[PDB]
Image (cartoon, rainbow, N blue to C red):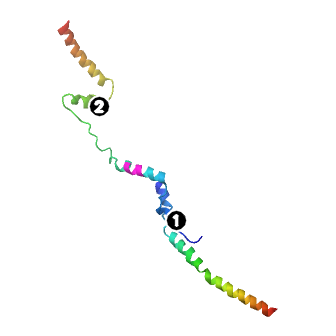
Amino acid sequence: VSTLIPPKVVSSKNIGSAPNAKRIANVVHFYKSLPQGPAPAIKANTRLARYKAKYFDGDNASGKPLWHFALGIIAFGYSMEYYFH
Amino acid sequence: DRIDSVSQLQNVAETTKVLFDVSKETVELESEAFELKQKVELAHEAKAVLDS
């Protein structure tokens, strides 16, 4: 009809409602993120925890970490047979 | 890509309203040409009477 403001209508809606939702998820995701792998908390030792944080730790995760249980139970069971048999 | 969607709007706020005004006021300046066409048509009519 006459003059208007075709571009200035970005007030009524920002570009990309789906991109806006994605970016809003991105802001919460990236902001509420550790600076560089923060909050590790690996070490622990209290009676059994000295074995948990050492033997159930994934630095090795080899076969001996489970085999310690077998060796210990064998130590218990040999005395069990000695007191039993 | 969100930054890119923002990239086009960077050098557009410079002259969006400038165009809004340039295409408005200069178009508003057409009443002068309208009235001048009116007088030119009156001149054509009278000149044609004289030519007759």
The question of residue B43 being in magenta is answered with no
Instruction: State how far apart marks 2 and 1 are (Cα).
Output: 60 Å
User: What's the chain of the residue with tag 1?
Assistant: A
Q: Residue at x 65, y 85 (%)?
A: B35
Q: Say the numbered circle drawn on residue A44.
A: none
- Residue stretch in magenta: A24-28
Same chain assignment for discs 2 and 1: yes
Circle 1: residue type:
Pro
Residue A78 visible to the viewer: yes
How far from the left and from the top, in percent, is residue A14?
A: 47, 58
Please tell me which residue lies in front, B50 or B12.
B50
Numbered circle sitting on residue A7: 1
Mark 2 belongs to which subunit? A
Residue underneath mark 2 = A57
Closer to the chain start, of discs 2 and 1, is 1
Amino acid of disc 2: Asp
- Label 2 CA crowd tier, 10 Å (few <14, some 14–19, many 20+): few
Q: Is residue A34 left or right of residue B33?
A: left
Q: Which marked residue is nearer to the observer: mark 2 or mark 1? A: 1
Please tell me which residue is depicted at 21% across the width and 9% down the height of the picture.
A81
Q: Position of residue B10 (x, y in %)?
A: 48, 64
Q: Quadrant of the C terminus of chain A?
A: top left
Image position of B23 with respect to B31: above or below = above
Under circle 2, the secondary element is loop
Q: Quadrant of residue B40?
A: bottom right
The answer to whether B46 appears left or right of A6 in the picture is right
Depicted B23 relative to depicted A82: above or below: below
Task: Give residue A46's position: percent from left, percent from top.
Answer: 19, 31
Mark 2 vs 1: CB contact within 8 A? no
Q: Which of B22/B27 is in front?
A: B27
